[PDB]
Image (cartoon, rainbow, N blue to C red; front, side):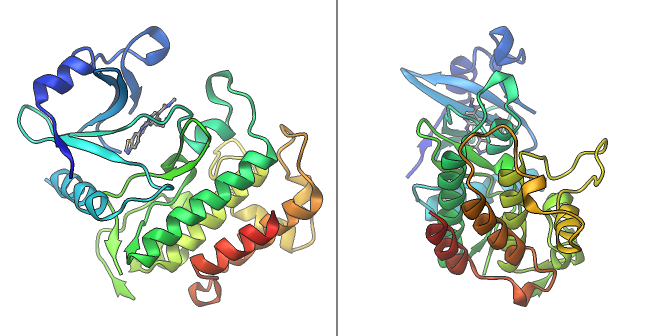
Length: 281
Ligand SMILES: CNC(=O)c1cnc(Nc2ccc3ncsc3c2)cc1N[C@H](CO)Cc1ccccc1
């Protein structure tokens, strides 16, 4: 299903894996462990990720991507087996990550509430496809929600994904986004819902999940500040938008709040998350 790319072709298309940043006219876009490069395969802009348990994540990415094709999931175009390093070739996402756009990285305009709602719905549609096809992402975060030309949400990074409550040694994921049970080693699609709840807070507030120079350092702690009636979600709403109405903001917050139940069985399933997000608009 995928194009097997030659290592010489990938070296050629990335200007010999030019490590200089894009900003400076280089090909390095980021750093997923390995470096992500901008490439041109004929007239097509691509993203080339040049990478023991790394070969496991490489195989898992191809395996999951072969089985999963959806409007709200990134597309793997091919890979490279021959040559010095393992490479993964993806479709270029012109608007990068939701994290980058929420942070207005490189002077991009803030996302409107209207775009944020479409992104929240799209990401939820992508998680629903994964859960319907018995996959647990395990690393749902704003950096893993990529954005195309129409700002369509595309879930990325399937290297840590697991088939679907089992427990494991070797706990993986991003702490600021992880459910309590996932931090304990449990493998459940219910952990993906918790991480999506944190993403919804990042969407409402424009705040990153973790900031060492902030009080509270962790975004999920704002839920407790709001719950303990110290503050309201209105005091946290991203100020970089002109179209956020109180009713739809509270509706998104109620969905995030439900996602963020510390008790995995009290959290809604992705299908309930989709329904509540569609009712919101
Ligand atoms: C302005 N546009 C971009 O910067 C951009 C364009 N296409 C991308 N494609 C793509 C699609 C699936 C995928 N799966 C794994 S890496 C990967 C890449 C990613 C992009 N940004 C991303 C986020 O900043 C770079 C990136 C940096 C560090 C780690 C991983 C990715």
